[PDB]
Length: 338
Ligand SMILES: Nc1ncnc2c1ncn2[C@@H]1O[C@H](COP(=O)(O)O)[C@@H](O)[C@H]1O
Ligand SMILES: [Zn+2]
Ligand SMILES: [Zn+2]
Image (cartoon, rainbow, N blue to C red):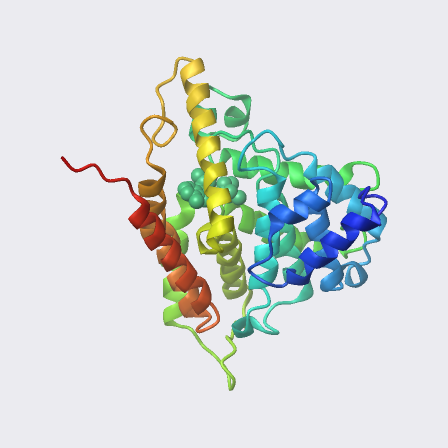
């Protein structure tokens, strides 16, 4: 309820204004955090579940849901500049919008929809603000536990599911044993897919599927087998995760400031511990503009272009914004003549 959020009517009214964009790409999650005592993930997730009647469908009481979500959100580190609950909220809301794209209407079951949004919400939980390689190079206990493979991603999953065991936190209590098994499988698949080292193989396989792309009498995509549906969900969450550059510049710029702050903080930690600094972690040798252009050209654009193709023409506006932002940064690159 509104009381669990500690929000008064004045801020509840502001929040109502902001939530008018719940199903839109233009929602401003920064404003949402500001009116919800900085609990953007729980607030947006509650709004999303209400909007999709997921609480009613899976018999999750508001009590259990809010208790779990508030617990999960508290396990995101508010001192980590980018990988915090604000980023998770953004990704969950972005996934929520992508799931409603015309080209995918009626394609996914409710359990698959539940799985993708949940995956998005927990995908970076308890992130330390440093990369897998940093954990590996410092002989971190986490790296040793997971044998240097998708260290953080494996940890995000373990924490997300482990927290269901705390008091009044099992939001999957009323799902059948079969549903829980299937949801777990799907969630694990999608979160492990957020590991950037799997990006290329994801894109490749994604393009391939687009070659075999099948539609209907209306333009709606056809995916009758699990394997094909999970590949789309997997890529959908990956796209939402990498959606910053496709948002209105006012938002994209705030995300970029955060990702750069987090990179510099890791650079500070490397210096503090006598380790050699990482690329783009050196606040004195990193070029924000150039980095963003490179990130879009080599990773984000190639990804969204393929997604745009799969859901043609649903994502066209997203691709255009992406391109405008890319050119804005391109022209923003500093210049020193003679
Ligand atoms: N705007 C951006 N510029 C450069 N790198 C980014 C940007 N947005 C996300 N990333 C990177 O994408 C990786 C995957 O995102 P995440 O799942 O949140 O960890 C992050 O670890 C960042 O290093
Ligand atoms: Zn991640
Ligand atoms: Zn993320």
